[PDB]
Amino acid sequence: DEIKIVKYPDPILRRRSEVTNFDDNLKRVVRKMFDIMYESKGIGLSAPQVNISKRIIVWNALYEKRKEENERIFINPSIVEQSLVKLKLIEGCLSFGIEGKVERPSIVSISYYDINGYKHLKILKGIHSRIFQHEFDHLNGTLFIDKMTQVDKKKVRPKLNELIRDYKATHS
Amino acid sequence: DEIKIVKYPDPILRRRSEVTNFDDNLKRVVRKMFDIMYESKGIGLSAPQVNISKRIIVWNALYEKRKEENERIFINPSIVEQSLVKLKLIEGCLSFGIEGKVERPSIVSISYYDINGYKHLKILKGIHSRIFQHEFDHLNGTLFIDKMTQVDKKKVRPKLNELIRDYKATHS
Amino acid sequence: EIKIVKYPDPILRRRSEVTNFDDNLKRVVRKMFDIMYESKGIGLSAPQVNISKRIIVWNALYEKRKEENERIFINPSIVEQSLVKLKLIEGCLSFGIEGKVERPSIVSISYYDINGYKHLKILKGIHSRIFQHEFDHLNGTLFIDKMTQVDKKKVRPKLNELIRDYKATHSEE
Amino acid sequence: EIKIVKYPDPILRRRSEVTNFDDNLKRVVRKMFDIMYESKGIGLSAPQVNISKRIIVWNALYEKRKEENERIFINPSIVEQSLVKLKLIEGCLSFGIEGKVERPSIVSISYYDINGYKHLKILKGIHSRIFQHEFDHLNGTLFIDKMTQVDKKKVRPKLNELIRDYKATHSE
Amino acid sequence: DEIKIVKYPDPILRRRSEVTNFDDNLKRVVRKMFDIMYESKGIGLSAPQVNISKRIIVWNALYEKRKEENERIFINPSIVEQSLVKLKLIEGCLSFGIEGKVERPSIVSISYYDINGYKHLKILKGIHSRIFQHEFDHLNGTLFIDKMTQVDKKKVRPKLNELIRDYKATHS
Amino acid sequence: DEIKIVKYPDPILRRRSEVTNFDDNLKRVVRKMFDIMYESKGIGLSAPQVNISKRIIVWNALYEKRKEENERIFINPSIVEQSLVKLKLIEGCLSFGIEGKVERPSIVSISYYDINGYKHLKILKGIHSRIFQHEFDHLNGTLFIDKMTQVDKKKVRPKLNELIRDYKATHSEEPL
Amino acid sequence: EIKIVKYPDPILRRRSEVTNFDDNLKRVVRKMFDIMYESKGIGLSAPQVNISKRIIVWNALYEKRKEENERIFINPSIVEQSLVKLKLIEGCLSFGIEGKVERPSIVSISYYDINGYKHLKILKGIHSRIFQHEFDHLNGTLFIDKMTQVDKKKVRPKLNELIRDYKATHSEE
Amino acid sequence: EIKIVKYPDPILRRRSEVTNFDDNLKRVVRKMFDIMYESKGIGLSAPQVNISKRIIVWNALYEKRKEENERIFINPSIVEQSLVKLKLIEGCLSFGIEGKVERPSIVSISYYDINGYKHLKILKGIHSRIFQHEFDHLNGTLFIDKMTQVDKKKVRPKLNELIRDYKA
Amino acid sequence: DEIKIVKYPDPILRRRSEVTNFDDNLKRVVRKMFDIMYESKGIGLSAPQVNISKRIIVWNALYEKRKEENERIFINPSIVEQSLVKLKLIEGCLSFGIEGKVERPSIVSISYYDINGYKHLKILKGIHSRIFQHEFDHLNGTLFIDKMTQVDKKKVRPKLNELIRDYKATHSEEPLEHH
Amino acid sequence: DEIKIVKYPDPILRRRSEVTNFDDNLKRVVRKMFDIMYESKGIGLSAPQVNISKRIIVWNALYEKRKEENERIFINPSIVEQSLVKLKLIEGCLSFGIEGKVERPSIVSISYYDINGYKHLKILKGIHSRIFQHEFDHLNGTLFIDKMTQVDKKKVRPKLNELIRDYKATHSEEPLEHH
Ligand SMILES: [Co+2]
Ligand SMILES: [Co+2]
Ligand SMILES: [Co+2]
Ligand SMILES: [Co+2]
Ligand SMILES: [Co+2]
Ligand SMILES: [Co+2]
Ligand SMILES: [Co+2]
Ligand SMILES: [Co+2]
Ligand SMILES: [Co+2]
Ligand SMILES: [Co+2]
C-alpha cells in the first residue's frame, strides 16, 4: 500500500509476483495502486511497481480524466491464447522516464480473477491488450526493455545508465 | 460432402474428425451443411453429421428465419479455456429424434480459423456457447448422450435402442 | 406459502406424499386457492406452492371467483381413462411457456375430500384436462414431458432461459 | 329365449363369455327385456335366459315399461367400488325368494353399448344395487351366496322346493 | 411370494437357480413375481430377483400398460440355438439403479416349459430376445455387469460400490 | 437342374447328401426343382429326388394353386429340437407312386440357410413340420418306407417290387 | 349315445360283439337313428355311436323322416353275393370325406329283428350298398380300405386333418 | 320228353346233372310245363320226364295257365333255410298218394335263369314248399322219404299198388 | 368325327388327351364337334366329350342363336398363368344331368394353336375363362365333380350313382342291373 | 426420386433391380420417372435409368403429346410366355444418343402390379411389346447393345467409346480425359 513508485534497477521489479489468495478487503491495495497511478499520470500499474510481489494489475485508458468503472482490475491473470499478427507500438512505463518500441501480439485471450474471487474470461484488443501485456510482464520480472528493439535499446542506453546511477547512490 | 444426414449409431459419429487444410473454394461444403440443417429444422450442425469427417462446425440461433452472416461458421476450432459456472440445459441433436439435459460450462474461450484460414480469438457465452460445445464434441466423437443426465439417459433409453435396431437394418 | 415455484426447482420432480391428517389445516388449501387466484391461473397443486403433499385445486371460472365452484382433490388416483385422446393447448404457473399436450379426454377417478371421505367421479371436461395436468404435478410429471416433439423443440430456448434465471439463486457471482 | 331359468340350473353357476359381435343381436336384448317385463322384475342377465354371455339389462321403473328408461350394459367391469356399504332387500327372477345382502353403495363401472362403444360411468343408488346383483350373475355368483346368515336360514324351505321343482328333469 | 426385490451384492444373485419340479398350484409365485415387477416399473423379472432360487422367467414388452396374456412366462428354460449376428443395446435391471450397453446375439432359439408342465419350442426375436437373455442369465448367476464394456464398467464403478455400501448395513 | 424325378430303387436316394457351398447364381437348380415337383403334382421335393446329391429342400403347401414366395426353400437344414409328442399321418412321395402312415413328431425346431446363405432359425409346426421331416430324411438317405408300420409296409409290398423290376430295365439288356 | 365317432378312433377298427339281450333297450336303436337324422346320414351302425355291438340301421329316404321306412338289422351275416360288382360313390358319417368303392350289386342276407327273431333276405340296390357299408363297420373295415389309389390320394389331406383333430381332442397341448 | 315216370322207376333215384348249355332248348322247359299242365300238376322236375337234368319248374296258378306266372329254376342250390319248420300235405306227380311232410317254411335260394344268368332269391310259402319238393327230385330224394312215421305206415298199401303197376 | 355324346362313367373321360399333329383336312372333326354341341344345348364341348382322345376345345358364349365365327376354337391348349382372384359359379356338363358350384380363377393367360397350326397367346376373362378351364380340365381327364364343393358333391351323389348304374347297362343283357 | 438420368457405362445399369415392396405413396418416384422422360424426348423408362435399382417400368407411346392415362405403369413384371414370331425393329435408349436394330419376339404374355399392388395379366402387342421387352431387360441388367446386330454394333463403336470416355470424366480432375 505504498506511495512508492519503484524504479528500473530495483531487484523487486525483476522478481516473480505471487498468486493472491485472500480475495477480500485489501481492495485498498487496489486503491493505493490506482492513487499512485493517477498521481504519476500513468496509464497502467502492477503491484510490483509499488513494492508488492502480488499478481495484481490495474489500468485506465482514460486516466487523464479519472472515473471509477473506467478502471480495469485483474487479479491472478494468465494469457490463455494470443494472436499471430504482432505489432510494434510505443510504450513507456512508470519505472522508467524512458520510451521506445516493443513488438507484441495484437490480440490476447485472457483469464483472470476479479476483486472478489470470481473468474472471468475475456478477449482484449486495442490499447487494452497493449497494456495488459505490459503490466502482465511486470508480474514475471520482464521489463519492456527486454522486449525492445536492438536499435532502440541503444537509442536509450544513456538514460538507462542515469537511472542505474541514481539507484547506485542509494542503500539505507 | 453430402445431403446425407447421419443418425446416431453410425460409427463415423465416433471417429475423430481431421483438421482442414485446403481452406478455399469449398464453401459449398459449408453450403451443403447449412442446407441439410435448414430443411431438417435444427439449430446447429457439424460436418460429421453430414458424413464428412472434417473439423467444421456451423450454426444459426435464428433458424426459423434464415439470414446470411447471421450464420456462424467455425473451421478448426479448439477450446482454450472455459468458465467455472456450468449450466444444465435441454439440448437437441439432428442425429437423434431425442432431446434432454447435459451439463456444460456457461462461457468458453474459443480459437478458430475462418473460411480463408485466418485465426480468430473469441469468447462465446449464452446460447452461442451452448451449441458450439455440442458441435465441438461431434468433431471429437463425443455424442451428447455421453454427457447427459442419469435421469434423462434412462428416460430416453428405449428410443436409443429403437434407433440402434433401425440402423441395424442397414445390412441384410 | 406465497411461493409459487418456477420450472427447474427440484421439488417439482419429487413424488408428492399422501395426506395423512385429513383435517383443520384447510388454510393450506386456502393458501393455494389464494395464490392460484392471485396469479391468474386455472389450476394448482401443492408442489407448485412448495409443499410435497398430494393436493389438487381448481376453478374453470377463476375470472369470477366463487367458493363452491372450487374443486378440491386430496390423495387422488386415476382408476380409468377414455381411449379417445385430445390435443389441447396448456400452460402452467411454474412456466411462462405454452404448448399442446395430448391427454385422454375422459378419466374415471378416485380421491378424498377435505374431510377424509373417499369419492368416485367421472371427470370429463376441462376438468378432465386440468386434473390430468395437476395430478401429474403430484408425480413429478410436467407438461413439457407430454408436449409434442415440435412444441418441445420450439420451446427449448425459453425453457433454458428459466434454467439461467433459476441458476441465479446461487448467483452472488 | 322365453326361457327364464331357475336356481339349481347349473348354467347360472358358469362364467358368461364376453360378447364379440356387437350387432343384430339386440333381439337377444329385446327378449331379455320382454321376459323381464312379463315376470315383474327390475333386472335381468343373459344366463337367466339360458345364454352364457356377459349381458346385463334393467329398468328401475318396470311398472311402466318405458324404453328411454331401459339400460343395457354389455361386457361390464367394476373398476372401483366404494368403501361405505349397504344392506338392502333383493329378489331375483331365478328365485321366488327375498332378502337382504350387503354391497357397496357406489360403483365405478366400464362397459360397452349395444353397438360396441366403450363408456365409463359411476352408478349409485338403485342402479348400483341392480348392477352389482346382475354383474354377479355373469360370474356364477347368485344372491343367496351373499345373503345374511339369518336370511339364508329363513329361506331354507323355498330353496329346497326349487331343487325339488327343478328335479323334474330325469324324473319323468 | 416375497416383495423382496434384491439388489447387486446379494449372494443369491450369483447362485445357479434350481430346476422346477412340481409344475402346479404355485401360480401365485408367478403372480407375486409379476406383482413385484409391476410396482418396480420393470420390463422383466427372474425368480432369484425375488429371493426364490428357482428357474422361472417372466416379462411384458408393454409393462407401462399392464394387460394379462401380454405376460410371457418361461419355466426351466434353455437356449437351443442363437444367431451369429450380434447386437449392442442399452440394458437396465431391477437389481441395479444402473444402466449399460451389453452385446447379445439378436435371435435365440428357445425350449421351455409352461405353467402346466408342457414343453414348448419357440424362436424369440427382437425385444423379446433381449430380455429373455437378460433374465436367463439370472438363472445361471450371470449379471449384466459381467458383460458390460470396460468403459461402461468403469463408468459405473461408484454405483456398484454404493450398492455394496448399502448392503453392508444389513449386517450393521 | 434336371427334369429327372428319380424313383425308389436308385442308389443315390440312399446316399448322404453333401453340404452346399456356392450360395449364389444357382437359383435355377432350385427353380427346376420346383418346376419338376409342380408338373408331377407333388407337395414337397429335395435335390436327390432330381439326381443332385445336395442338401437342398423345397415345398409348397398349396401346389394346386402355385404362387411365388408361397413356396418354401431350405439350404443345409438341421434339426435342433423336436417335440416329444408324435403323430401318425399318411404321407406320399414323388419317388414312390405309393402312400402310407408314418409317425414323426409334431413340432421341429430348425436351422438352415437361405438362397443367399444367411443362417436362419425357425419353428415348423404342422404340415410344414410334416413335409420338412419327409424331405430332410432324403438328404440322409432315409426313405419313408423304413419309418412305416408292418401293415402299411406289407400292403405296399407288390408296388415296390414293380418299382424294383422297373429299375432293372435301366440296364434291360435281356427279356429278364 | 350322441357319441358320433370319427375316423381315427380305434373302436372303428375293432370286432363288434353279438347282441344278446334282445329286449327293452330299443331306445339305443332310436338313439342311433336320432344321431343319424341330425348328421343327415343315410346309414349308421353301432360302432359309430361308440357301441361295440352288431347293429345296422338306415333309412334310404332320410330327407323324409318316417318310421317303417327305417331298416334295423341285428347280428347280420352275408350268405351269398352277386358275381357282378359296382363302383359307387360312398359317404360315411365318421368322415366329412367322399369316394368310390367296388362292392357286389346284390347280397343274400341272414339277420335278426329287434325282438330276437331270425330273418332271411335279399338286398338289392342302394339297400345292398348301405348294408355292405355298415356291415363292414361291424368288422372294423372302413371304406378307405376298399377305396382306390386315385381316390385314396385325393382324400389323404382330409384324412390327416381328421387325425390331427383327433390327437388334439385328448391332449390339446 | 313226354310221359311222367312213376314211383319205382330207378331213374327217380339218380342224381340229376347240372345244365351246361343255357340254349335255345327252352323247348325242354316248355314240354315240362305241357306235361305238367295236362296232369293238372302244380310242379314238375326234369327227372320226372326222364331228363336227368337239374331243372325245376312250377306254376302256383296252373289252374289258369299264364306264361309270366311260370317259375323256372336251372341249377338250383339251397344256401340257407329257416329255423321254423312246417308240416304240410304234399303230393307228387309220380304218385296218386298224398300226405304230410315237415320242411322249413322259408328258403334262401340261388339258381340260374333260362339264359345262364345267376340269381339269388327268398322263396317263402308255396314256392318254398314246391321248390323243396322238386329240388329233392334232382337229388333222387322222394317225398315219401321225408314223410311222417304216421303217414308212411298209413300209405304203404298204395305204394305196393304202384310197385305192382311197374310190372307186366 | 363322332355323333355320340359321352357320359360320366365312360373311362375315356379320364384318359389324357393326346397332342394334335396333322393340322389339316379335319375341320369336320371340329365341325361335327360343333354340330353335336348345338343339338345338345350345351355351351362348349371338348373332343373326349364326343369320344376323341385328342386335345381340342370349342365354344360359343351365345349358342342359343347359332352364329358361325362367333364360335371359338382352341387346339392344343395350355394354361400359362391364372388369376389369384377365384370365383364360384354354377357349372354343368354334357356328360352329366348334374349341376353345381366349382371354384376356379377369374382370369386366365392362355396359349393355344389354330386350326391351321399357328400358335397364339390370349388372356381369357369372365365366362370365356370359365368355359376354357372346364373344357381344358376334360383334356387332362379332370371332371367338374373333382372341383365341386363338399356340399354340392354330397347333394348330387344319388344322381352321380344313378348315372353309374345307367352306364352299367352297356353289358346288361343280364338282369343284375336295374332301372 | 432422381432427376439423374444415367448413361451407358454406369455399373448400376448392369445390376439386377430389387422387387418393389411397399406399394404406396411413392407415385412421385414414378412421376419423377415420367418427368425426365418427356424432357429427354423419350418413349420409355425403367428405374435403374434414373438411378433407382427397383423393378419399375413406365412408358408413353405418344409423348409428343403427353397425356395422363396414356402413360403405362408396370410394377414388378415378368414374362410368362413370348411369341415364336420375332422382329427386327429399330430401337434407341435414353442412356445412349445411339440407335440400332434388335430382334425381339412380336408378342409377350405379361403379369405385373399397378401402383397399388394388384396383380394383372396382359397381352402386349406391337410398340407396347417392344418398349416393354427393352425396358424389362434394364431391370435384369441387360442392355440393348447386347442384343443389337453384328452390323449395327460395329457401326456404333465410336459413340459407345465416346460415352465410355465421357463417363470416365466422372473421376477426371485429370485433364487427359477431355473430349
Ligand atoms: Co511498466
Ligand atoms: Co449433435
Ligand atoms: Co401446473
Ligand atoms: Co338375479
Ligand atoms: Co436383471
Ligand atoms: Co419323398
Ligand atoms: Co360308414
Ligand atoms: Co314230386
Ligand atoms: Co364338360
Ligand atoms: Co433403354
Image (cartoon, coloured by chain):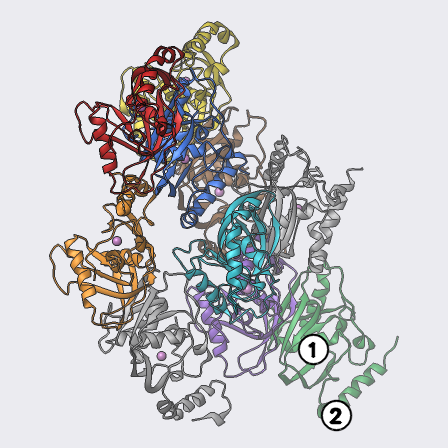
Chain colours: A green, B purple, C brown, D yellow, F cyan, G blue, H red, I orange
Of F76 and B166, nearer the camera is F76
Name the quadrant containing residue B80: bottom right
Image check: D58 left or right of B74? Answer: left
Horizontal and vertical percent for residue C73? 49, 31
Mark 1: secondary structure? helix
Q: What residue would you read off at disc 2? A: A154
Task: Give above or below for G140 relative to A24.
Answer: above
Neighbour class for label 1 at 10 Å: few (<14), some, many (≥20)?
Answer: many
Instruction: Indicate which quadrant contains ligand 4.
Output: top left
> Which residue appears farthest toward the front when viewing the image?
H168
Q: In this view, does C50 lie to the left or right of A50?
A: left
* Mark 2: C-beta under 8 Å from nearest atom of ligand 1: no
Question: As displayed, is residue I136 above or below residue B118?
Answer: above
Q: Do the residues labelled 2 and 1 touch (CB within 8 Å)?
A: no
Amino acid at dot 2: Lys
Between F163 and B37, the one lying in front of the other is F163
Q: Distance between the residues labelled 2 and 1?
A: 21 Å
Under 8 Å from ligand 1: the CB of mark 1?
yes
Residue I24 spot, x, y in % from top left: 22, 72
**In front here: D153 or B31?**
D153
In the rendered image, the vertical position of residue I23 relative to residue A98, given as above or below:
above
Q: Report if residue A166 is visible in the image.
A: yes
Q: What residue type is labelled 1?
A: His
What is the x, y in percent for residue H6?
30, 24
Residue, x 42% and y 44% (percent of image)? G147
Question: Is the residue marked by circle 2 packed among few (<14), some (14-19), or many (20+) residues within 10 Å?
Answer: few
* Chain for numbered disc 2: A
Checking the image for residue A134, the label placed there is: 1
Q: Which residue shows up at 38% across the image and 11% down it?
A: H153
Mark 2: which secondary structure? helix
Mark whose residue sits in front, 2 or 1: 1
